[PDB]
Image 1: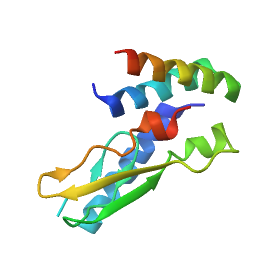
Image 2: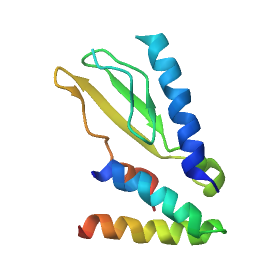
Image 3: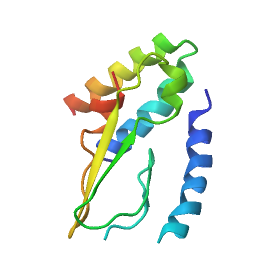
Image 4: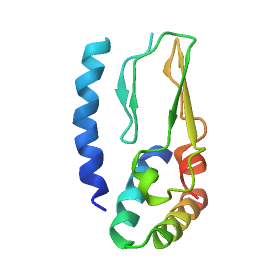
Length: 85
Length: 38
């Protein structure tokens, strides 16, 4: 698996639609593309798409961030706790 | 280099070592323990 290159393609793919959408800014955390958001709303994402292939039989992973006055919050849970093993 | 930084780095390091997925999980399990220990 050439994960670093797939992530990078996705990072360019990410900046492409952040600009279309634009509260918290659209952002790329180096794992996930976060569609920009209003203060007070919560965005869920799933584990990176690579894992659909790496561990096919596991698909319950969710990661959340809140958009606050102080910008995006930390991931919850952390990517290690929600997408690692 | 924060929790998220280390997970991305973990992914790419393990994805390069492992050629079977169960090797991948193991290297990834190890990368989580390094993260918690640190």
